[PDB]
Image 1 (cartoon, rainbow, N blue to C red):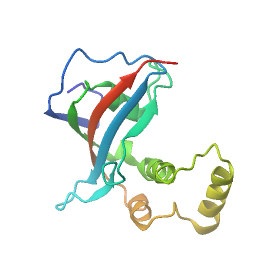
Image 2 (cartoon, one colour):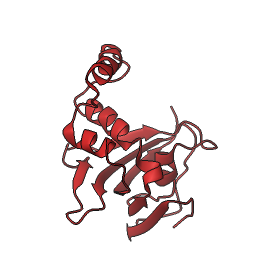
Image 3 (cartoon, one colour):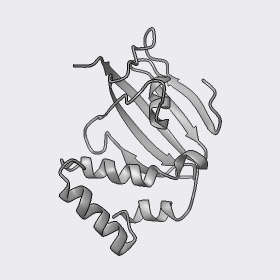
Length: 155
């Protein structure tokens, strides 16, 4: 449980080793599920449900994006639960939208999608999914459960 404020880690399955080489430009490979902190612990996104593990790449190790903070605190095969206070979760709807887009084999590269995406948002005032929309308009803490599967060093 490393400290960074508004964030509570809880390691579930300890996972093996000596903390990987989280070098800028390493490729982090993982599954995650994200849930509300309600009674049902409602799921919102679950990479296992979409059938495949998520992948990010480390922009800069000295300037970590918030998700990288979480990932970088984990060993391979570790399974941890991260509670995150409302201050960190404002963006998640926009993230999720970007993930669900990626989930159908299309990239903000493709530029229709980046352009046409923004067009829909502005015109209709929606990220394109009710849950994400409800959640947008109802700020909230969340729980992420992440399973780190792999870290690979740069090309």
